[PDB]
Amino acid sequence: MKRAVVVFSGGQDSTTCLIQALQDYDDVHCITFDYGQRHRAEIEVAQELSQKLGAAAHKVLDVGLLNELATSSLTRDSIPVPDNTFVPGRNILFLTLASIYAYQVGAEAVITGVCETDFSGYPDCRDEFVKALNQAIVLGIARDIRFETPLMWLNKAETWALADYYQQLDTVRYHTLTCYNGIKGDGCGQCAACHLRANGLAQYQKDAATVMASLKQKVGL
Amino acid sequence: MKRAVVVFSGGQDSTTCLIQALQDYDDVHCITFDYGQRHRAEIEVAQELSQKLGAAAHKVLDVGLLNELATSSLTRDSIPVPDNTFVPGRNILFLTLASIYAYQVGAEAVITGVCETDFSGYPDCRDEFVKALNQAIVLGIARDIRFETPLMWLNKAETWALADYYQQLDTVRYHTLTCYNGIKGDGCGQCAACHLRANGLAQYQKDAATVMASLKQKVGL
Ligand SMILES: [Zn+2]
Ligand SMILES: [Zn+2]
């Protein structure tokens, strides 16, 4: 049983990792980290998506303790902070919980859609970080689980190409949720996340062969 | 502000780390990870203990999502497992959450009472592991927080010596909770944890100078 765990939220990136994973592994589980997120029903849609794509299971794990670690919460719980909703290292948490889950279901790999190519560069999403953490977790859980980051070096246009490579661009396009305002697919067209995704799609459509060439060159294939 | 975070449960080990930390730092926070643990009132006693010892704050964080990761829970939530209550890597979690907390309250160190000298050797409690994780977390949170493990190389007798070195053996002895059955201090005398602790105390009383010598030799002082 060659089996993987996909850190999954039902958006373009994580559904593109799931689609690729379903070709490369015999068995794929999805895990979703719910901290306020979406809502029961959106998470439930993402579960129908994974179910309908072929995931063997989809665990939804409440990580609302993250929100307890925001400065506003801490000050509210009478904790002194030095004089935001920002919480550091959330992906350290996610990768740790996915590994514990992977251990328990016999998965050899945790797959995550993090990358270094966005405007904002989160240090818990850097290639160097993920490798460093992988090495620590392997020691702490006493098992060799790999961390895979198929989207590490990809821009959005290339991510669209990858979906297309597995012949599923339209699945991603119609049936995922990227929009901050809850609109599936192409979304409201008016939020940050809609812009990023739509720019990507439009570069890919204009210059497909070039972007596909770029994609193949970076990832193997 | 030289400030530390003590991973704290109100037992002998974590109260010994707190006592030492209160000499070495200007400000100490305690964090307790509650997953079923004790109960509101015991946790509340451990909070009076920290308050009365001088902690500047004591955060109690619900980590009951750990229990959701046990095989019995997963099978109950209709997740396939390969055909216990055991959960791997719980201290990877604890150290990650303490670091996030330390970041938010401006702490330069997370202090933990883990060790390699017990009958059972948990790989998420090994010196090599803690260093490996420290290195990863520093990258993921973008700040140099140290992980300190004052009890790493100590047996129980030496841990008692350390309390005694800070002139607080009786505080640990009467006012902490090690016993599995909820009995403070010397406890029921009939559980594993009572035995370990009482053996320790009795070696320390029989051969004090020798054990103190051993302690000093390992930790500095
Ligand atoms: Zn939108
Ligand atoms: Zn007992």
Image: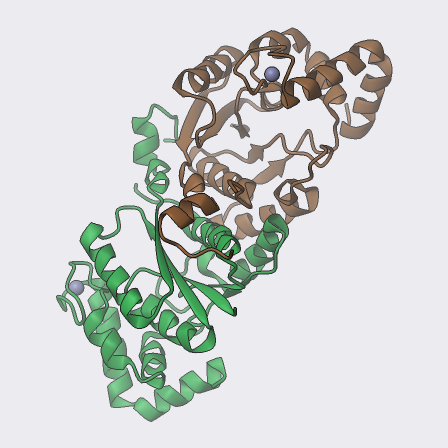
Chain colours: A brown, B green
Q: Quadrant of residue B28?
A: bottom left
Query: Total marks drawn?
Result: 0
Relative horizontal placement of residue B221, taking residue B86 as reference (left or right): right
Q: Is residue B133 above or below residue A91?
A: below
Q: Is residue B111 visible?
A: no
- What x and y, as percent, mark residue B60? 33, 51
Q: Is residue A97 above or below residue A60?
A: below
Which residue is found at the position 75% from the left and 17% from the top? A199
Location of residue A166 (image quadrant):
top right
Say whether residue B92 is left or right of residue B51: right
Residue at figure coordinates x 44%, y 68% from the top left: B27
Decide if residue A31 is in sight here. Answer: yes
Left or right for B107, reference A74: right
What's the residue at 51%, 38% (across, down)?
A: A94
Please tell me in which quarter of the rendered image ligand 2 is found: bottom left
Q: Position of residue A9 (x, y in %)?
A: 52, 24
The vertical placement of A107 against A181, above or below, is: below
Q: Position of residue A208 (x, y in %)?
A: 82, 12
Q: At 64% across and 33% down in the image, what residue appears?
A: A114
Residue extending farthest to the front is A83
